[PDB]
Image: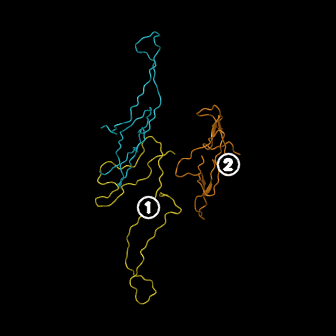
Chain colours: A orange, B yellow, C cyan
Amino acid sequence: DEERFFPSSGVLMFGKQGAGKDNVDYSAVMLTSEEEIKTTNPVATEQYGVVADNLQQNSAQPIVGAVNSQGALPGMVWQNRDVYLQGPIWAKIPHTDGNFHPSP
Amino acid sequence: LMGGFGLKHPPPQILIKNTPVPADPPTTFSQAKLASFITQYSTGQVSVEIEWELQKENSKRWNPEIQYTSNYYKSTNVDFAVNVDGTYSEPRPIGTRYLTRNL
Amino acid sequence: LMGGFGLKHPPPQILIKNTPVPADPPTTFSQAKLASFITQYSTGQVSVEIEWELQKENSKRWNPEIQYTSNYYKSTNVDFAVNVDGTYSEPRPIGTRYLTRNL
């Protein structure tokens, strides 16, 4: 029930026919939406979750901090970003010693 | 994390020991284990041979690449050589990354 | 004495010329050779391929040898590359003598 919000750089943005290069109004752009993956994927704007920040004791009330960035944990499952009629088909995986889930 | 090749079944450990040779026992039986041995050491030669596979450099780069080079200028000692007193030293770390590639 | 390989039968000379195409002659006969020609030039591609034999380096030297290296430090231009205006240059002479041998 929030379609007005989108992550700042976190979504693909296509222009309508005849859109300029620079400082174009919101009306000429077309924003995509990844909401289909909100089943397995955390929302881009919101936190991942909360974890304990301290050791608890009768003199110390529990404190729980927010996790804004989370690397891979055993037991995670996720969806890749969607592909679009006007979007890119492929990319070259860089040639490197290691990579993680090399989907563009 | 220090470097090199991670191996599930790495080269095995090679364990060596001088077999103990006891000195003369008491001539009347005692159950205690023998604590008196002949002092010994051993010497010898060890040889190890590794076959390494190489990945050749296919680069189409035009300009010359950086190489590892010995300094041309004069010095009291040669790098990677013995000195006057006869001891061998390695003057610097030599990494393996010189040639280049594209991502 | 400048360098390279002396050859009794070197690669032959390859001579090329535009065949002359004369303009219209006088329509009455004249013995004089025709001095009036159509201005022409020609372009094309030339390809040359040489096979070189190599003599590999057998040296048993322990310490590392001097190599030809590109300078690691930053610069406005890459050596042996085009500049902003697009012209190619060779910044230095590169000789062939780096590895060493015993007399």
Residues flagged by tags 2 and 1 on a common chain: no
Q: What residue do we see at 60% from left, 54% from top?
A: A66
Please identify the quarter of the rendering in which residue B23 is found.
bottom left
Q: Nearer the viewer, residue B10 or A73?
A: B10
Q: Nearer the viewer, residue A56 or A11?
A: A11
- Residue B100 rendering spot, x and y as whole percentages: 46, 46
Q: Nearer the viewer, residue C83 or B38?
A: B38
The outermost residue toward the right is A1
The outermost residue toward the top is C28
Label at residue B21: none
- Residue B95 rendering spot, x and y as whole percentages: 43, 53
Residue matched to label 2? A37
Chain designation of label 1: B
Q: Amino acid at mark 1?
A: Glu
Chain designation of label 2: A
Against C22, residue B49 (above or below) is below
Q: Nearer the viewer, residue A24 or C9?
A: C9
Residue matched to label 1? B49
Q: Label 1 near label 2: C-beta < 8 Å? A: no
